[PDB]
Image: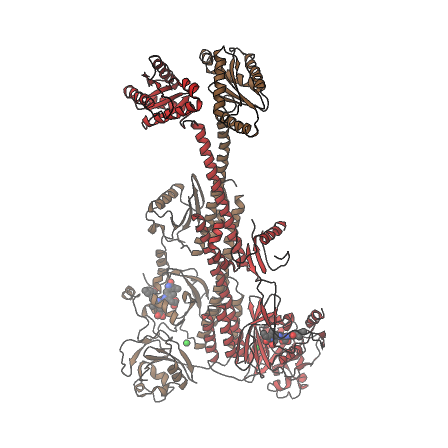
Chain colours: A red, B brown
Amino acid sequence: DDISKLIAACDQEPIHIPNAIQPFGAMLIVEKDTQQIVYASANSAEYFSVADNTIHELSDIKQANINSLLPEHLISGLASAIRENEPIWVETDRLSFLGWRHENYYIIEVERYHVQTSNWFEIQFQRAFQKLRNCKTHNDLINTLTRLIQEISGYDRVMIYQFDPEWNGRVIAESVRQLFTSMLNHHFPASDIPAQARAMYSINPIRIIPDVNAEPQPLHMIHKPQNTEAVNLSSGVLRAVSPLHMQYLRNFGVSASTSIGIFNEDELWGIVACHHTKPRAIGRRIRRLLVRTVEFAAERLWLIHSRNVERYMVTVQAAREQLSTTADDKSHEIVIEHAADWCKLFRCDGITTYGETPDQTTINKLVEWLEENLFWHSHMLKEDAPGRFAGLLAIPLLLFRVAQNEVRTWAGKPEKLSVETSTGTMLGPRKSFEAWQDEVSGKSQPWRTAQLYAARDIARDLLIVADVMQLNLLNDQLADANENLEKLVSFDDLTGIFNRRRMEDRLESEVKEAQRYKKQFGILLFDLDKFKSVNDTYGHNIGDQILQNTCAAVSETLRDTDKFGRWGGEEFLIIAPQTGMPELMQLGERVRAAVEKMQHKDLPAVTISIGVAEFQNDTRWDHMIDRADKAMYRAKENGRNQVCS
Amino acid sequence: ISKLIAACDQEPIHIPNAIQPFGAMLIVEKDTQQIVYASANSAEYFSVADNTIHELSDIKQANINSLLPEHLISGLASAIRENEPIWVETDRLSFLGWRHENYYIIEVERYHVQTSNWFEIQFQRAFQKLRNCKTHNDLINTLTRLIQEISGYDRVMIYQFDPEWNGRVIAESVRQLFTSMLNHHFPASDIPAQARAMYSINPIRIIPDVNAEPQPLHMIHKPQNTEAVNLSSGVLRAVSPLHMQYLRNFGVSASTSIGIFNEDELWGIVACHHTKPRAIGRRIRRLLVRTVEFAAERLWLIHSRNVERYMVTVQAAREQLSTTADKHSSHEIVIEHAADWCKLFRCDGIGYLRGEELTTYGETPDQTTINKLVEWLEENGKKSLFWHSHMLKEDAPGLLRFAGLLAIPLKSDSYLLLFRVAQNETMLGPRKSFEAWQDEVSGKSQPWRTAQLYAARDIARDLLIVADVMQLNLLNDQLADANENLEKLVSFDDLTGIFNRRRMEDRLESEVKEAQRYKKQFGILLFDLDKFKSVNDTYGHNIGDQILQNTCAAVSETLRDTDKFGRWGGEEFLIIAPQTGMPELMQLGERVRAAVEKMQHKDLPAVTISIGVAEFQNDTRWDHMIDRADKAMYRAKENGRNQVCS
Ligand SMILES: *C/C=C1/C(=C/c2[nH]c(/C=C3[NH+]=C(/C=C4/NC(=O)C(C=C)=C4C)C(C)=C\3CCC(=O)O)c(CCC(=O)O)c2C)NC(=O)[C@H]1C
Ligand SMILES: *C/C=C1/C(=C/c2[nH]c(/C=C3[NH+]=C(/C=C4\NC(=O)C(C=C)=C4C)C(C)=C\3CCC(=O)O)c(CCC(=O)O)c2C)NC(=O)[C@H]1C
Ligand SMILES: [Cl-]
Ligand SMILES: [Cl-]
């Protein structure tokens, strides 16, 4: 647009080489090699006449010698300087000199000066420093800075102007003695300080305009220089002001100004702006006191910001420990317990949902577009199909910010003014600074890096905890399946007692022990009597029901050492360790009587015939089963329901 | 001198009732406005305000308005806060006064106007140079050099206090007119609590001449309160003769020191020694203190940004652990990164124990000692908590070289340890002091600063988690692998590779239900080996079992694909034949019985089966069918073996 073109044209004016100065001093430019005064400001006579009573008009300077004009210390100091743009301050009783070396030149600015002897500045320094050290908060620091600067400088209005990333500004603190309207929280456009001017603070942190209506004095050529290109003046204070900005200050109701740049390392963070409603000069000592105060206040402010980051990281670690304590006691469960805390942690509105969120369907459309296209974070990109909501940080392996329309007050409505300057046609300054409002529909707060990494860390721990609940559940269920399939391999489905295999194993180990340690044990091998008659007359279901009954009757009779299992078909085995043949036969009698006398329960009466064997220094368990077996068979021959050895 | 060293810590240095002679002092009662004390040399300074003051006694005739400026009196009258000195100058005299309880204390010094920009230039240069420092080191060295350039003192040092109030000289700027003091430590006893506390009242202390004769306070008029007045808010307060002697033994004739405050905490001191007496005016004092104050705020900003970079480092390490896990073991990860963790935790060694495995890096005791430590922790009951010490020999007595230990307990289905090496490398003096400090840190490790501890619990948290995940994943792989084998054992038979008893009960039950839904027709064939006990006992188990395998091999080739064939009990088998009526069912039974008869003997006996057969006859339970097929099987067995019966 034509606006953009006009604002860009401001950069054409070379504000560092205006070949003129403000008239609150005088300036000489001297060629180092020839030691010849090559430039003098039109007002040089009225200052250097004090050094040289032969100086009457400007033209007399051409006839003068610099040793007649400069103090001894300034001359030696300029000769000694190898580094460029390092001003040297040297005073007489009536003049105050600031000189520096720039390429081939020495630039010397001189101001009239009165000697003034007191501890005022030292007391100011101690008090300002103590008051800034006492600030614990961004707010307290910036307001303390505004009051300190106003009291030191005496300016009618003092502001803290903070730059945003696009170089627009907001006034964040203010102190206004006389009747002025409050510019507090007013926004200013980037055009108001072009890049070329913001760049000045890096050469000299203070800029002084003691009189917006003072007539600039141009530099006149005295002797001819070997190079006629304009000399850079930006290191001093006397450099002339772009009439655009003189007019800007006029339109602002300001008659004199001073500003100091606020630097975070090499970055211009903002400025301290000082307006006065009548002309006002400030001496070199008040200037130094100002810049030192802003520099001490800035280090303090950055320290305050840095401590805020530490406090926030402590909160993040308290959150990650809280998450860890909850997961051990009880993953969406984890999300529900702490989300009110997390909303503070992440300065977000919505978080399975909590706080302000889209409905499940819109949330799934969100998810889906991310699946189509790490985390993702932005405030109202509008790069998708809208669902109210403007900020989203989504870690799929969701954090929501509602749009927050922000009314901004500007210091004047914009104007597309044109002005004809020397360097071309460019934007003229707005005529009104009256308050004027816009708002940003559809944007959210930007994501701070500290919040970003806290969020990536909370999501990382959550994913791990879901994985651990997972693996623990799968271990519980595979362990349960292994429990069932291991019971099925060892026991018999019907009767729920050791199958043949487990009885062979137990019997084998009882034999090995008894052979190793000379222990005594015996086995009981019994069978159900006339069982086929039960099966054919009553059926297998009734017969199997009898097998279950008989197992229940046998298991209640046995001692804790004995092991009881199903050997084959309707044959069962009992292993009685630490039992001699007498008590062994006794156990066979109690068992035999137990199966006879059990409850019939609408089923036939049942009898078992038991053979018995004793450990007789045997090698293998197979022999013992044979003895108990043929013994059982003699029990079958003498009439069933018997115990035989 | 020794008798004084016996009781130096108790000495009340704030109330010596004397001043150093680089000025004079008046003490005035606030209410009556009477001079009640004057320093013994008061005549020579106040003779300047009042040329009638000849001896000290003339002060008794004086009125405070005759000696003090109007600005000083009104400023004192308006002050409600105590101990905030007020600086007021005349053409010949320089006044500092403050209110303390009942009194106004006024210190006065002779004074000379400096008309020059020397101070503003010095200050700007100091600020620029400190602002250029990006590191702790650069800042402390720049500050020592600047303080020397401003104060003019032959030697300038920065003492940093440790948590126990010991001090270390960490920067120095010294003409070789003195010996180098860099890295010397002094014990906390060398600056008593009362002397460290004075910096909070006045940040600067000046001793222009160790050999100047102190001037006592004399009573001028009588005070309503007879107790000694506290003088600590000014600069003239007299110096403990013990410490004057300390500086004498050191070759120091004058000193200045400034406190370095982190908020209200005394972090260290800027000490300035000179080899001959040396005065410093009020403007140089203020310039010095302002410089230390700007430098201190800078240093705290540098430390705070270092904390930020350290937390970024910790987070980069915990992500690295997660990247490394993707190794087969937990001890594999520890071996790869423990040197980084030693940097991360500022410790000399680490040991990780997990079940039967032990890993060490750096300086550690041998494995056995590590087991004595573990056991002693789990014995004290202190195992479950975190535990840490910077003095093992006194905290954990009797475990003999190493001095620091941080032990993180880890619990699953079990430790991470950090080891730190001890610190090692009668006239008053810094040689006795440096060996006094050696005694205080004997067996004491560097204390565990808090930022490293939480780095350790957080690194350990991920270690326990990743070890647990490798564990649970391996154990789940093993439980899943075994269940396949135990599922082969539950559904199949050991010797025949054919369905178990269970699988035939289940198949039969489900076949009955299925036939019950669609009124479909199926039958079962129940066969047995004939005189098999006689075969087993005549030929043995090896031959007999191979016969069972032979018979299963022969039958499986007989079956149709729909039929299900399983081993029912002992030597009894079942065939479930879907889509088969009783005629075709009997046909299948004859083919099966004949199939088992003609098989290869292979030097083994001839074998025959007897088959019962049953058909689905509107049955409820699989029980009824087994009974029917069973009685049929028995009629075949009874009527001459090798038969099929319905
Ligand atoms: C038990 C009390 C003692 C004591 C008292 C005392 N000291 C000071 C001032 C000191 N003393 C310092 C001690 C040092 N330790 C060292 O290793 C070195 C060597 C470089 C020194 C100097 C010390 C550092 C200070 C302050 C700074 C300075 O160096 O000046 C005071 C305060 C004096 C006052 O002005 O009131 C007291 C009371 N001195 C001890 O040595 C022990 C015995
Ligand atoms: C096309 C060029 C434009 C232009 C030029 C311009 N502006 C400056 C200097 C300043 N502008 C400032 C702006 C503010 N002053 C305030 O008090 C506030 C309130 C918060 C703002 C936003 C400031 C502070 C300066 C510095 C000078 C000063 O301190 O007063 C210059 C450079 C001036 C110089 O030193 O030569 C130039 C060239 N401004 C535009 O509006 C357009 C027209
Ligand atoms: Cl200046
Ligand atoms: Cl002082």
Closer to us: B215 or B608 = B608
Q: Relative to A358, is A423 above or below?
A: below
Q: Is residue B367 left or right of residue B602?
A: left
Q: In the rendered view of the protein, which quadrant contains the C terminus of chain A?
A: top left
Query: Residue B401, position in %: x, y?
Result: 38, 48
Q: Is residue A246 left or right of residue B81?
A: right
Closer to us: B25 or A214 = A214
Query: Residue A356, position in %: x, y?
Result: 54, 58
Query: Residue A492, position in %: x, y?
Result: 43, 26
Whereabouts is ligand 1, in terms of quadrant? bottom left
Q: How many marks?
A: 0
Q: Relative to B469, is A71 above or below?
A: below
Instruction: Farthest residue to the front: give it.
Output: B618
Q: Is residue B334 visible?
A: no
Closer to us: B49 or A132 = A132
Q: Is residue B459 visible?
A: yes
Q: Relative to B168, is A569 above or below?
A: above
